[PDB]
Amino acid sequence: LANGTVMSGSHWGVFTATVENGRATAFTPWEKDPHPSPMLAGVLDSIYSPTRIKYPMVRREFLEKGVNADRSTRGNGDFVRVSWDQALDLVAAEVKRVEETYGPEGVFGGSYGWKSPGRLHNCTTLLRRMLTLAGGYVNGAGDYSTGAAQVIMPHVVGTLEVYEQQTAWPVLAENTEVMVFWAADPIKTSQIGWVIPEHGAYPGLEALKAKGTKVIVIDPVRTKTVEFFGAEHITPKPQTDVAIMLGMAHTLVAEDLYDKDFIANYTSGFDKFLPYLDGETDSTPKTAEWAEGISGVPAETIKELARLFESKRTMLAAGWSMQRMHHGEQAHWMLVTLASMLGQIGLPGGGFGLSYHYSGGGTPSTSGPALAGITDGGAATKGPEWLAASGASVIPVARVVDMLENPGAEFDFNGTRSKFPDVKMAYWVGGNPFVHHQDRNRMVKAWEKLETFVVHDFQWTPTARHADIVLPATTSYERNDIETIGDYSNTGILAMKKIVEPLYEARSDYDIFAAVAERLGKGAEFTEGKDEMGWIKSFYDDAAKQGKAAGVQMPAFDAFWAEGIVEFPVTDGADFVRYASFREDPLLNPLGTPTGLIEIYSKNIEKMGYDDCPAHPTWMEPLERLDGPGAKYPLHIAASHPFNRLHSQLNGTVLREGYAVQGHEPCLMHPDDAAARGIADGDVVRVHNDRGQILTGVKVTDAVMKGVIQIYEGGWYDPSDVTEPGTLDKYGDVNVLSADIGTSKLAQGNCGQTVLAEVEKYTGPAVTLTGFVAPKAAE
Ligand SMILES: NC1=NC(=O)C2=N[C@H]3C(S)=C(SO)[C@@H](COP(=O)(O)OP(=O)(O)OC[C@H]4O[C@@H](n5cnc6c(=O)[nH]c(N)nc65)[C@H](O)[C@@H]4O)O[C@H]3NC2=N1
Ligand SMILES: NC1=NC(=O)C2=N[C@H]3C(S)=C(S)[C@@H](COP(=O)(O)OP(=O)(O)OC[C@H]4O[C@@H](n5cnc6c(=O)[nH]c(N)nc65)[C@H](O)[C@@H]4O)O[C@H]3NC2=N1
Ligand SMILES: [Mo+6]
Ligand SMILES: [O]
């Protein structure tokens, strides 16, 4: 049996595995990783945990009745174990039947999800590769992270902005005087990467603290970011950040401090925004005192913050939670507008940055080449013949349930009108929509419209428990692959080597789709005559020929594989200043906006005439907010990203023991809010509102501000009874309480953090958790 060490990587970093008699027994972090993540131990455990999917399973009702099956029982665990040949035939038959009967509009292939890194074993692209050969599919656009901000930014600054390289960390160390983390917890969220992370922000944060720079955190929760710096902490009522920004802007106008030259030469439309700010249009001057009444943040604090930002070199590093809410578009639009008034855009250490908390943004980029990977083939096809009627071929990701509920209906998106297709089948790989999507009870009922639902995963998630057909996938650690280290830095290329043999009857997504493509008569088209190592060698060889051309030397494929990693050099990467060239000469280097300047007022958005997205940053009442006029529930749920999970990943591993409270997902509550309900620390509680009800376990702390509770997203939904409408979730999936609505007509983003609820001590009948053990028939 195999004994030795093997280096690989993941979403949590680079590591070395210890293998003993063919079993991975420890994962040790890479020696050059400046800040390893404590979740590595959970990654290892994820391979062997009790929720690992062993065999291909078919839903008993679906097996016996096909499309006439009762669809209300999806999720009850009544599965039938089948052979791979049986399951593959069924999957291929169903894909073919739906394509022939309904056309490409009948198959939803968006399959949103964080999957695993790797250029070959990219399950979502592999699924689209197969669906392409099958006749077509409906896809998803945008994402659940910057759903509103990625659509508003291009109308304001010209590009996406959120997924672009930031002013380098070192530039910040020598020039920044005031660092503001606005709705950002970089310490918590910098642990993972889309591709292998280099954890480059930790060293960057460490240099700011060593320099003694003043740090301000604006967040309702006292996070590790606050604690790490001993920062001045401002706690607004969730969803009122725009009110505070207007209050600050108003102060800068009233005391005549803002930068008129900056505004005059680099922006457009300020004069159309001024009247609103002064109350000329609505009779409501947006003062610091007016902001105080809405946000709860003292008027004088708001004025002192405004003045400090204007007199010191300030960097506004904003997170994404505050645009994952109703009217999300205004949050970063107003932030840029405030940034414009301060006049530091394009100066070393000043301006704003939207990716300092995500995937190493700000870590100096190397001069290394770009790495490519398997494609879905669409760019060299001549896909479906599509047209309105049948409907749109692309929907904004968060409108999947609206689509199911309203086939043929029209919807708005960024100035256009399209129709919802009539989807009959959904195929999901590498995602967990039964945890990640909003308003669980609404979505549980809307799923009944799908005849067939196919899922691949290696863990028994809520999504997999609800499938008609479940196929067991392998982890990254049971195969070979290649991937980039550093989403922005491009630190190097890593060989992701196989650690152990596939467990049970698990198969890679690639092999599964290969076999399904074979049954549709398209085997060679899918595989291209290459095997695993042939694909990986061609990605590397292409990068090397690109490297060569640019003067970067790279070893031959087998030399690279023997080493396991290539590292690229940093040349001018550490001196990068975002927007510097625009500041230096705006006429020669203008933005990609109609006017070529920062658009505070948008004529383009004006012509769309959307009620929920005015032509300039505006304060608007959200669906529900803490202490809002007529608010029905009293507590705001900060349903943010989990510290010891990657979304739902690693919930069914040994890490859960360290944070669960009586077996349930933890809930942070302030002592005063606990006292009022006669709630003691460690008690099981019922959290509920009009959309659903869930059980969590309380942790009493003053880390959360009064009026706010913290229940992280990602908990595995564990319904008491799937056939009972609004059944109680026994574990703690925060998305059973959120609403499923668009941010506005412009972006249609998710409003996953626009949630209010009530909490009461749980006194009902004892409950048995069943989400962390495999379905009985799957053992
Ligand atoms: N109320 C909410 N608040 C929020 O803040 C919140 N966040 C969003 C955002 S920001 C995201 S990402 O943009 C989504 C993430 O949902 P996702 O389904 O990507 O989550 P995961 O728990 O990472 O599911 C991944 C899934 O894939 C499996 N897997 C891994 N490797 C592969 C593979 O190679 N083969 C297969 N077939 N499967 C793979 C994992 O095991 C895992 O189950 O959440 C939003 N919701 C929010 N709500
Ligand atoms: N460890 C960890 N696990 C993860 O699951 C995770 N996921 C990754 C992904 S996919 C992304 S897209 C990003 C998300 O990065 P993002 O900035 O969207 O993260 P959140 O955890 O949702 O919110 C961050 C902070 O915003 C605060 N906040 C909430 N609402 C308000 C409010 O209205 N006003 C203010 N001022 N602040 C508020 C929260 O309290 C929290 O500390 O993180 C990434 N990093 C990840 N880290
Ligand atoms: Mo995200
Ligand atoms: O994401």
Image: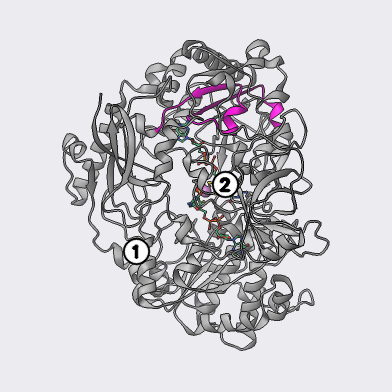
Measure the alpha-carbon separation of dots 1 and 2.
31 Å
The answer to whether the beta carbon of the residue marked 2 is less than 8 Å from any atom of ligand 2 is: no
Residue ID for mark 1: 203
Q: Amino acid at mark 2?
A: Ala
**Segment tinted magenta in the rendering:** 446-475
Tell me, yes or no, whether the highlighted magenta stretch contains residue 454.
yes
Confirm whether residue 413 shows in the render: no
- Determine the secondary structure under disc 1: helix
- In the shown orientation, is residue 129 left or right of residue 289? left
- In the shown orientation, is residue 80 left or right of residue 412? left
Q: How is the image coloured?
A: one colour
Q: Position of residue 159 (x, y in %)?
A: 49, 57
Task: Using the image as rendered, state which of residue 17 and residue 67 is in the foreground.
Answer: 17
> Image quarter for residue 173?
bottom left
- Determine the secondary structure under disc 2: loop
Give the vertical position of 507 relative to 198 (above or below): above
Q: Amino acid at mark 1?
A: Pro
> Image quarter for residue 246?
bottom right
Q: Position of residue 144 (x, y in %)?
A: 57, 47
**Image quarter (top left, top right, bottom left or bottom right) of the N terminus:** top left
Confirm whether residue 204 shows in the render: yes
Marks 1 and 2: CB-CB under 8 Å?
Answer: no
Q: In the current view of this chain or complex, which residue is farthest to the bottom?
A: 255
Give the vertical position of 254 relative to 586 (above or below): below
For label 2, the crowd category at 10 Å Cα-Cα, with few meaning under 14, some 14 to 19 and many 20 or more, is: some
Q: Which of disc 2 and disc 1 is earlier in sequence?
A: 1
In percent of the image, x 67 and y 16: which residue is there?
61
